[PDB]
Amino acid sequence: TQSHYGQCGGIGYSGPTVCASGTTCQVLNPAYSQCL
Image (tube, rainbow, N blue to C red):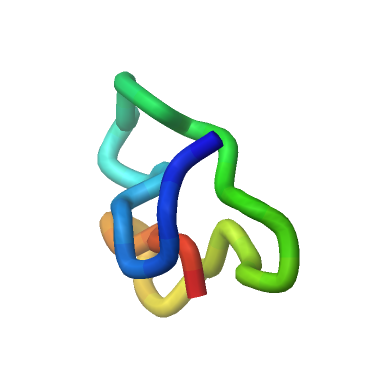
């Protein structure tokens, strides 16, 4: 899984798109899905 503060999604986003537990794959803005 992806670590705390590591980016998860948003801007048609590739790479480690699956967060660690406790933290959420966020939706702060359309581009900004992060592990918070």
